[PDB]
Amino acid sequence: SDAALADATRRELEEEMGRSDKPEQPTPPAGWQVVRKPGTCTFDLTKSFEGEDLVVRYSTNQDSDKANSHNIFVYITQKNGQTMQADLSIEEGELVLNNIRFYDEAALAKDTGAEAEAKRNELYTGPLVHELDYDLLNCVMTYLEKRGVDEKLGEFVVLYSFWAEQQDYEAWLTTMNKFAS
Amino acid sequence: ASDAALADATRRELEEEMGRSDKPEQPTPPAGWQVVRKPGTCTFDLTKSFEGEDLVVRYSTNQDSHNIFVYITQKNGQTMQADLSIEEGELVLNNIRFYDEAALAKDTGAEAEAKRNELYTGPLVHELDYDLLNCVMTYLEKRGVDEKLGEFVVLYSFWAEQQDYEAWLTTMNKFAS
Amino acid sequence: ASDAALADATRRELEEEMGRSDKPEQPTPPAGWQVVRKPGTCTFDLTKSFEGEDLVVRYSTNQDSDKANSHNIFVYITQKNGQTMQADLSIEEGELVLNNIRFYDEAALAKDTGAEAEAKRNELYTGPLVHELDYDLLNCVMTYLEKRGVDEKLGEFVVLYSFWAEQQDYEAWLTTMNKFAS
Image (cartoon, rainbow over all chains, first blue to last red; front, side, top):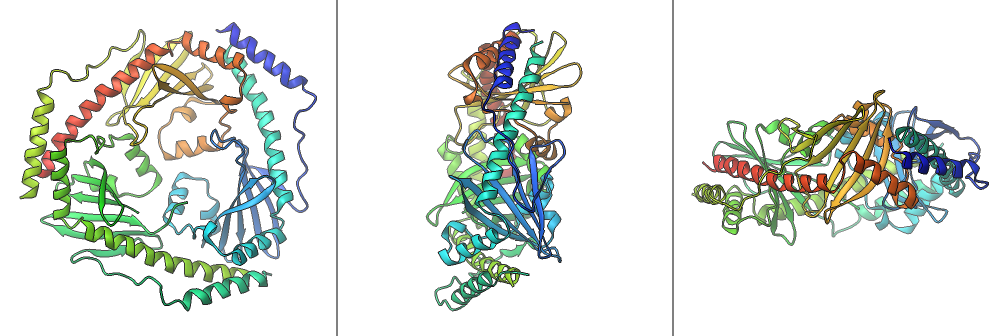
């Protein structure tokens, strides 16, 4: 259809494929296994810890609002199903805790369904974390840090995202070029 | 197994909450209104009948990083939904809409919400003819949806939020030991 | 009775509205497009074919409490094999502004309504940030959309149709509240 759009996308593809400074895929930290949820931009870091199942979830999708936004959702599940969820953002290489809540069953915490989110929306989301004592919140940070949820992992998530966004952008340019053919 | 420093900090925090003498007390609702939570949630419904109509003032007791939804159902099924904000003890009408049946209106759940987002949400209440706006507010105040109710909802949600926070520390404590 | 004064109030407003001679006229859609309402809703699809492609421009005549100035549209371009581009644009000052471009392997994945359909899309790659794209590429996308009838004339239609449809729903709303008060 549009020769001009095919040319613009072709050149961009050529610019990207020829770069000598594309983001390098980072190496995950010790103990964690990266598992992309099939077909999506969602990834689950996982590992066991003293009988607990740990999951660190994050999307490589970019938010058109806060471009520097790098949110993560960490789930810590006990043998009886009791799960803690901690929401953190990665801001200037540091982890910032934004929410802490609990669920009776692991499945309801990690389910990606719309009806599951609606279930979770009804429950108690926890207190306003930015209004908690330094001692309590700092202990929660250390508790997470000892389990591997630390600044090195935040760095990995950010570097992995830059890398994945680059590959997806290349795929996006290819598809756009196909549409302009 | 777990982490003792967090067990102690949550324990210390629990001691401080249970030792307070300035904690919010559970207020009582205005006459007729039956307070009933949805099992295992922070959603609360104040229900009662009024001249054949089934009323429901719904609010959540969770905080965001005070709003109510008033459902008025006719015997036919016709349901009005009034979204109100509790500013300084007083009420501010923000939205008015309608549904053929009470199910679609009150139904929580993702799919029910999606259907609602597709339907006409109503005119902008602020642009409405002021004589009609008066009459709707009178219409609501007659059914007990007034500044006395907006007062309860506020005080009640403070109370429920203290309870959930205490259970949250108990849960987190149990979690770290 | 208070619910009797509401009846009189809605009845007076309906009479008022029904007797106006300055109400919004329903606009005429640009060439090729067909207007089709999603039954019972404020969602509308403008459909048309162009060089084997199935085009859909989707919008709602509902207005946001705060955003009573912007009009969002979702443009779908579906190929023969089902692969579908979605372009999100806003209409501001009679000007089309491009806010997002993304692709899907299948048409239903892109265009299905519902909570679950949205949630599935929420997990997929939504495309790059449009602000960070080069002028050349983004300008060529705008032209590409323009060739297909997605231009300022289409935007003006949507704006005009929203004003008209909003008046119609308000009138139905007055009747329904009046019924409620009767």
